[PDB]
Amino acid sequence: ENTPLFSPSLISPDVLAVLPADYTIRPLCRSDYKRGYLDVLRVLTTVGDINEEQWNSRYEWIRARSDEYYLLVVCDGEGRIVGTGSLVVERKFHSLGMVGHIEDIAVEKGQQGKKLGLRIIQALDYVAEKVGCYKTILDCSEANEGFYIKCGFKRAGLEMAHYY
Amino acid sequence: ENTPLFSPSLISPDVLAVLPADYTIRPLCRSDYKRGYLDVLRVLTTVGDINEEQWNSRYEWIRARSDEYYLLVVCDGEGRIVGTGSLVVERKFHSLGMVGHIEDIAVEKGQQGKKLGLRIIQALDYVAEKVGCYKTILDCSEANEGFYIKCGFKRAGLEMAHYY
Ligand SMILES: CC(=O)SCCNC(=O)CCNC(=O)[C@H](O)C(C)(C)COP(=O)(O)OP(=O)(O)OC[C@H]1O[C@@H](n2cnc3c(N)ncnc32)[C@H](O)[C@@H]1OP(=O)(O)O
Ligand SMILES: CC(=O)SCCNC(=O)CCNC(=O)[C@H](O)C(C)(C)COP(=O)(O)OP(=O)(O)OC[C@H]1O[C@@H](n2cnc3c(N)ncnc32)[C@H](O)[C@@H]1OP(=O)(O)O
Ligand SMILES: Clc1ccccc1-c1nnc[nH]1
Image 1 (spheres, chains in turn red, orange):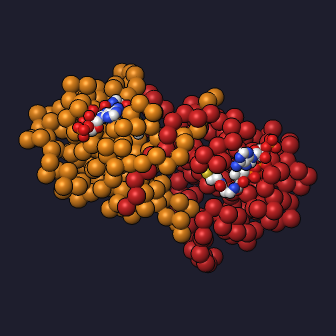
Image 2: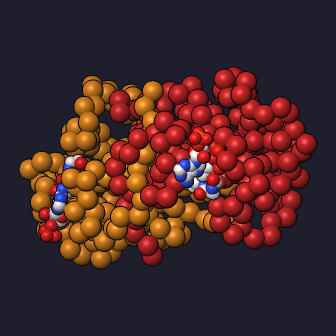
Image 3: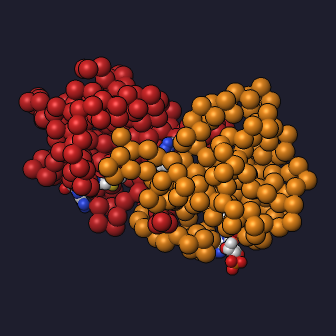
């Protein structure tokens, strides 16, 4: 239940080197249910009650796709998840090339503005580079553009949406 | 080898109703190697030589992920693929919700400006709706924004990119 979602060898040594004392960034593991992962997600959207059975099934589902869905967490060294982010690696049918997609970055409100979001993005960029992505992309609002600029991203196009 | 990538029941009846005579939109199948699929892709990027062995292996790879990677084609009714597009369905770890991502839309140059790109997008939107996506998103350049506006998309944010 402490078996990481993906290899810890995919975590940037340079990011680990600059985290606050006792903090770590690491792959999700199944035991993170107990470390307040869903609480960090509540920064992003309303989540809902989820029980350990459901968590365990959703964890086996993502683990079946661990060559695509890279979920990592920032742990405060006291058993509390305080940040998360996702890299989804799109393996094309670019001479069969690969694009990383950054998704669902969240930092607990009380821990915001301490570079933990930057560290999460640096870590997801390092995963994507390591697995052979030529680029990482993400969609953002006009309001958090300046966050992604500080993380070394540049405007590349427009996000278009269609609602049902 | 005529076994479709995904169920033909996911193809919009309304789109099939308005295609030019003898044209169809349908899931990719393994035999599409022989119908000039790679030629349509050359509208998007430079592809390279790929042999039938490689095609067959890449086809089994996508078929293993046919709950995520929905590739469809426009067939002219004379054995020629003249358009393609992809829907990638992102199943979240939104109360475990789903986002469609439209990718790699291409229409052969000689068949452009006849509504085949619109039909491809309408068809991919219908797949996403049917499988339970709350929204479909895509990234585009400023130059083809007006194409997506005509297909019923609206600007929703910015695409940011990070190169290696
Ligand atoms: C692709 C997606 O994930 S979109 C969803 C993004 N997530 C959310 O909107 C959820 C709510 N917000 C958050 O969780 C956080 O505020 C995040 C993840 C956006 C940013 O994380 P934080 O830990 O707060 O930011 P962090 O301190 O790492 O920011 C790095 C730098 O960007 C700055 N910054 C942070 N947010 C913003 C912003 N919205 N606009 C401009 N600058 C910003 C920080 O002040 C810091 O600047 P510095 O280098 O000059 O110190
Ligand atoms: C998310 C992604 O896939 S990004 C990659 C997009 N693909 C490419 O750039 C590859 C090259 N381009 C193409 O293959 C095609 O031109 C496509 C797929 C962009 C559009 O396909 P087409 O079949 O040419 O367009 P289609 O005739 O369906 O266009 C529908 C309407 O939009 C119009 N239109 C098409 N392209 C554009 C454009 N770039 N700007 C504004 N309007 C456009 C058409 O004239 C038509 O207008 P109407 O309803 O008034 O007749
Ligand atoms: Cl294409 C895409 C775009 C944005 C977010 C995720 C995806 C994806 N899901 N599986 C593979 N790729």
